[PDB]
Image 1: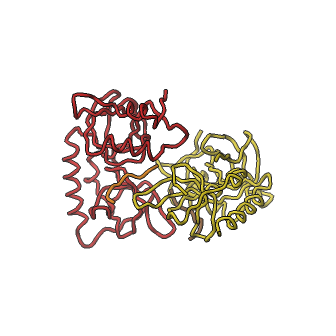
Image 2: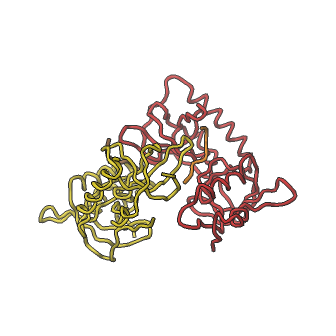
Length: 191
Length: 196
Length: 8
Length: 8
């Protein structure tokens, strides 16, 4: 079993929808290129069929049941707990949940061809005012992205994620999300 | 409210007991210097008395804020930092003197007072130096072997590198005349790879 | 509930 | 069960 993440070039502009959020320094996006959304749905349907009819190791791929919507999804084992439960990282969305052994199944190799789609992002050129992202800053960021396709520009590519500049183009007046957070005193400039 | 961690000098040698374990790249130690274990016992006693009283405190959770949090593992209150706030309304807390993170409810949190923040935070994040996982993740086997090298033992730690978030250490077992460097064990046994 | 925001 | 090892 081997796999990959969505790949990018530096300064690539691409449309995104935020699929999971923790802070302005940690949120997850579906990158809307190469028929991603459609291929991911197709894959998810194949998984529901396959799972409808596993030895845990850290970093190992699997199918895991997500109780939030009651469907099976691609995951990697993140933690193994004393209880015998396992925390899994849902690789196409970016959330982590604690599941039981019954909520895990081995994944088939042909299910690892589509690149993993929960791409970790952070907004470039900002930092927390103090040491940690506040609820207010994150809540405001969330208000800026909820229900929206945004333009993302990939500014920096690291092994563990991508620093992006996000712009809302839903009206003729473009709105760069960092602008809002800086202007409203919620985060400090950085870089 | 402000606080500190335990502080070190490069190449400082100091006895440790491991208080929390996740991997060879992530474990937590009590460093046995400056009467730490005793001052930490005394603080915890003081937190039990303070937390015990009716009414409890109105605590407002904010990320990275210090508090007192109830640990259901042993039923006592300890020092903590807010790590996460969950949709349910529950809060994950980092127990700062031990290194574990637990999900608690709002009745299991109380505001902390400045006099309880004088003692430096004692759960020091560590990693063993000069090793790396064979692939990209620490195996259960590598982690359980490591645990079997430290359980119930006081070890010598040499602080080789200091970063903002923790310390890289070399750990040696001196409980017999034959010193045992824990990394040697893990490398020899093929459970981890040399690094550097 | 589902994939709800978690403050971190 | 108390502060038990958690594999990560």
